[PDB]
Every structure is written in structure tokens, then in C-alpha cells.
Image (spheres, coloured by chain):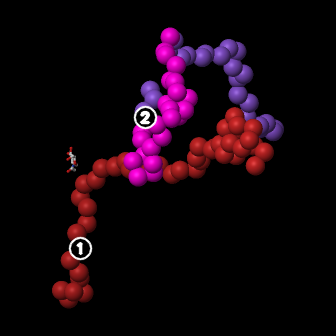
Chain colours: A purple, B red
Amino acid sequence: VYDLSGFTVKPVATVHRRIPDLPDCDIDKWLNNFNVPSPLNWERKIFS
Amino acid sequence: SVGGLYEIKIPTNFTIVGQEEFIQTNSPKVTIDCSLFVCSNYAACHDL
Ligand SMILES: *[C@@H]1O[C@H](CO)[C@@H](O)[C@H](O)[C@H]1NC(C)=O
């Protein structure tokens, strides 16, 4: 009597969830802003 | 010994007493799938 290697049931479908209708982050507009700071006064922006 | 005789307590009445004794002779037959335990469903782990 041989105990074979364990199987797992195959997933029959995919569930994908995301919050709809969120705005674009505009990260490029902030990175391309020509008023660039020095390392002494490095700027932060938070995207959520 | 008082002369040739010794003092002894001899029973004048009795009963029967029961005593239980469990002796283990077996144990749960544990079996491990080493591959399923170590790596679960993950192909990248099964390779390593
Ligand atoms: C023996 O002990 C039992 C329980 O105490 C009692 O019922 C019985 O009468 C006694 N017999 C004698 C001969 O003492």
C-alpha cells in the first residue's frame, strides 16, 4: 500500500476585487515638476 | 517473643477490592506527507 503524493483541488474560477472609479495618482506630474528640491530639503508626496 | 510466642495481627474479616490498571499497547499512527508539509501547492518550492 503506497500513500501517493498529496494533490490539491484545482481552482474552478478567479475572484478579482479592486475599488472602482479611483482617480489617477499623477505621479509623473509631481516627478516632472521643474521646481526640483536639493537633498538638504528633499520633498515627500504620499499617494493613496 | 513471650516465651516461644510472638504477637501477630491476623485478619478476622475480609472483603474483595477491585483495582483498575490501564496499559497502553498502541498509539495514533501519525503519517506525514513531507512534500505537502514542506512546500504546500507551490511549484517553486517543490523544485528547490
Ligand atoms: C464482616 O464485615 C462485613 C462488613 O463490615 C459485615 O457485614 C459482616 O457481618 C462481618 N462479618 C464478621 C464475621 O465480622
User: At numbered mark 2, what does the secondary structure look like: helix, strand or loop?
Assistant: loop
**A36 vs A29: above or below:** below
A42 to the left or right of B15:
right
Q: Circle 2 is placed at which residue position? A: A45
User: At numbered mark 1, what does the secondary structure look like: helix, strand or loop?
Assistant: loop
B8 to the left or right of A14:
left
On what subunit does the disc labeled 2 rest?
A
Front one among A33 and A24? A33
Front one among B26 and B37? B37
Under mark 2, the amino acid is: Lys
Quick one: which residue is furthest to the front in this view?
A34
Quick one: which residue is furthest to the top in this view?
A21
Q: Which of marks 2 and 1 is in front?
A: 2
Question: Which numbered disc covers residue B8?
Answer: 1
Question: Which numbered disc covers residue A25?
Answer: none
**B10 vs A12: above or below:** below
The magenta segment is A21-44
Under mark 1, the amino acid is: Ile
How far across and how far down the image is residue A10, in percent?
A: 72, 22
